[PDB]
Image (cartoon, rainbow, N blue to C red):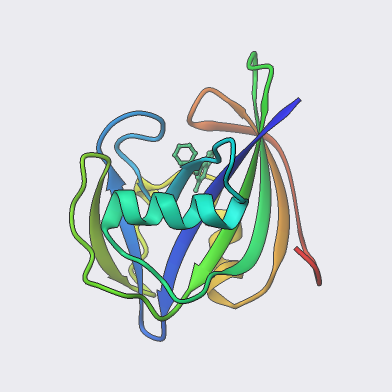
Length: 154
Ligand SMILES: Nc1nc(SCCc2ccccc2)c2[nH]cnc2n1
């Protein structure tokens, strides 16, 4: 029992783009751009769709960099999140109803105002390593169990 989601990180040589989530799931935390994958689109098409909806950006190419599975206590469906990276983007990011975008220097990442699992795997993304992760949550703040490894194929 699982459902597909996407997450996109725009990572340039000296900065990374994050959005402050204004409503819905994860509101009040900085994150990459993404959401549910729809019927009739590929996983990559869904990532591009969410990036455009939430920031206005389009891209030449997306690269697969990780997979993370989330379990929330008392929720029947696991979340299967496919994580993508890009350097080159097309456009200037703008605010949407869902997200307020800002650039961050790579030594000033706001981990205290991010999902707690990001402190574990985001460092691997910044180091350009591919990864598989699993995190079990009780509510939105408490990690009960986790696994994390580097992989050769995402
Ligand atoms: N960084 C991060 N992201 C997510 S969900 C990302 C994808 C998403 C899904 C549904 C609505 C909008 C966005 C997380 N969940 C639990 N820990 C987490 N960490």
